Length: 100
Ligand SMILES: O=C(O)CCn1nc(-c2cccnc2)ccc1=O
Ligand SMILES: [Zn+2]
Ligand SMILES: [Zn+2]
Ligand SMILES: [Zn+2]
Image (cartoon, rainbow, N blue to C red):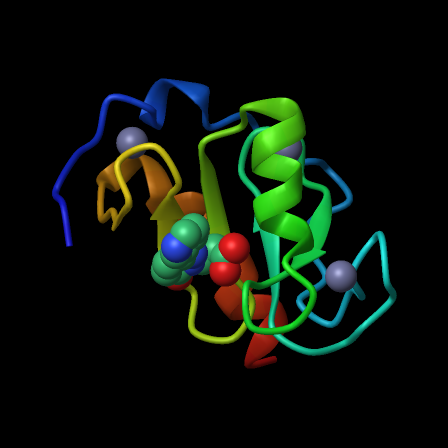
């Protein structure tokens, strides 16, 4: 996993409502394998379910998404996981909500 990527600048402030790691996919409502967009904080399912976060990436261009299964962050442009101090606040909020 990368220690930086050129899309970290697109990570936006966490909503004051916080994160809900049990939030269903905004398109198909599935509770399985969802991700949260780190630009707009919409929640959509992963590639192995109905691929709605990949569709969101396509229709918005938003780069970075956070897994509600394992709190990894994937950048769709870099095609890699990313670890950076800039992602700690959001991973921590998600971790607190998930575990707790
Ligand atoms: O499931 C998603 O939509 C995002 C998360 N993610 N996406 C991919 C991926 C994306 C597009 C094409 N091939 C692989 C690879 C690893 C990963 O963690
Ligand atoms: Zn879905
Ligand atoms: Zn988005
Ligand atoms: Zn990137």
